Length: 144
Length: 72
Image (cartoon, one colour):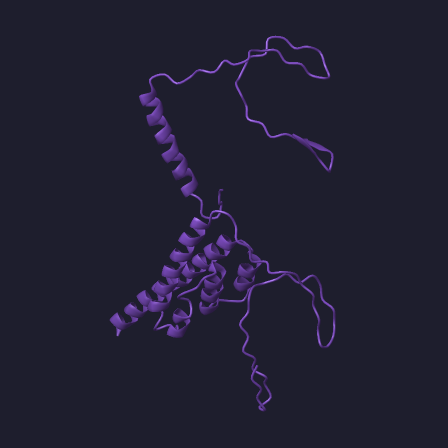
């Protein structure tokens, strides 16, 4: 927790897992009570690891091709060598850029495989958009 | 077998053999008639073993089709 005199207290936080919020107790400052982590490890972990590997490959392809779309390499370097599949899933989900409603939908999914499938679908959608961007850019340079 | 605290009779069993009911004795409690065992043991075990292997492979393919519908 590093402190600055400019007016912003930038705190370096490394989180653990999501948890549900029962209700809201007003402040300020605000208060809210929760429970234990909602991330759970279900049965059939072979499919879990297969989906983890597939999502890792998909995100590697997504980041590598997205250089014209300004995707950083430190984000790709921070997802290698992970123990918890939830760690890899959330780390990749943060490093991929989309809206906040889809991030909320991902965080709602307590299933270890549902979150992976949703991230895979979002990455596929963004990669299709990227392919469309590449095709239209090729058309633009051809027109030039 | 045992009794659960919520008022349920639990019993762990393995089925022995199928049989045909001849007549129904009035109940409750229900009564059943039949035979002790009427199963058919394997004959020409080559085809039986081939079918067992094929069914094992087909069940592995059945369980391999799940991506968000995980099975034990």
